[PDB]
Amino acid sequence: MYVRISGRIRLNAHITKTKVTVRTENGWTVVEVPAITGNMLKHWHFVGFVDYFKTTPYGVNLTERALRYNGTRFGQGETTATKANGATVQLNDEATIIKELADADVHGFLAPKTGRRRVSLVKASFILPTEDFIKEVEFSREYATGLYGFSIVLDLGLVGIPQGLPVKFEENQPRPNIVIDPNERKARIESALKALIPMLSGYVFKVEELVAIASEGPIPALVHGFYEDYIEANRSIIKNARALGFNIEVFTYNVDLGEDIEATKVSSVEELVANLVKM
Image (cartoon, rainbow, N blue to C red; front, top):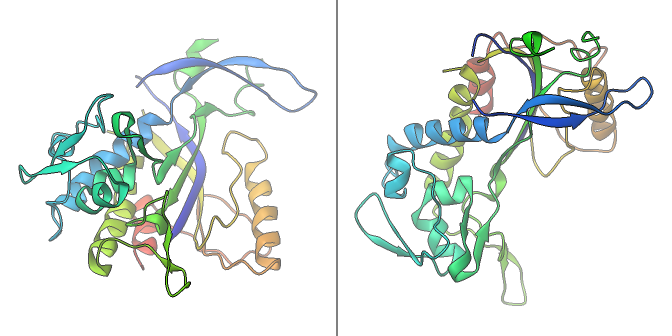
């Protein structure tokens, strides 16, 4: 229900690149390095989510814009949105918006004219050349190909649930405030997991290694693949969180993690995804 993934990609002969400053343990040196916004990966998750959610019985619960992969959700002065239907949806009430529009549910929205906001359930940090790939430099050249760290977070437990009103009451008794039936909820979650395949495919990108983990509450967070450290760091986080009582499925792709985290080696992203869609 809650998924985090950290790992590394290799670039090749080719995407918005910008400059960031970063460190680089072994003393503290701040170094300006090229980087790629997480929105790259979020955009591609969003295309696949649409492509997978389309084909479900619910695929009509999408903004018309999402069907052309247009992610303007919403304009600064917009008060309505057109459903893939052609129906009009008021942007008044997060419950209504997310009930009708699964792209706003899963990928969030902004409606400043009505004062409504939903943080995206799909998050992606900056993609950054590795602490250890820097250091080997001791320069573009190498950065244009090169080894980049990433990190992704999927808070899928909040699908169908407004963030400004997660629970409703009476008789003085809190209930989760879920505004879509259980099957649409499920279709939306599977689609948000299967969308991981094109989010990570390429289509500039080979996935070299990653660590992924389960649910069912913000669990713990992972260390970003940037750190030379990160695999050992994630080992510690995981065996500590397990020791404390958190229940956590772990999956790995070309990484060891070690002796002995109960883990599950996969041979590909597809296989990871396949494992996740376990519901």
